[PDB]
Length: 124
Ligand SMILES: [Au+]
Image (cartoon, rainbow, N blue to C red; front, side, top):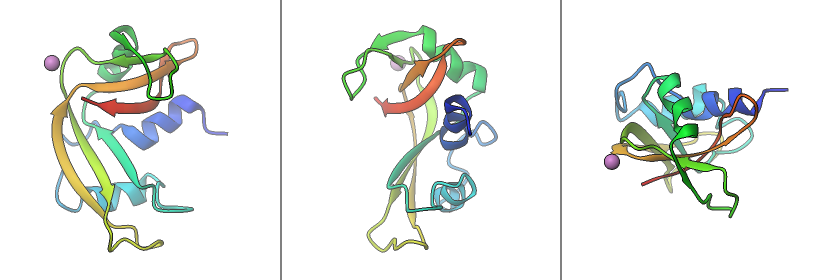
């Protein structure tokens, strides 16, 4: 069983690229990170920062989670992110995505000991 922390790193971390490598990025990364396996994951965000910098958000600004839980944290600094958004043309198993790059504050849900990111909640 994949740990919640490892699943967060697979679904949301991409420290290799500074920003949305290309117009191809989401099509390749949604597939390579196994987010198009059983269905086309409809939206997903990748963060282009060090793992240590993303883990550190669990000690930053405490905010409400979209689901009403209290364990979400907002980054004090903006981070380089890529939003991936499934198109209309997109029909499983040929999942098609729009790659958008932005610099935004991330919001992540944290749990455990050690206290680490487990859920990408939002960017603002
Ligand atoms: Au800011």
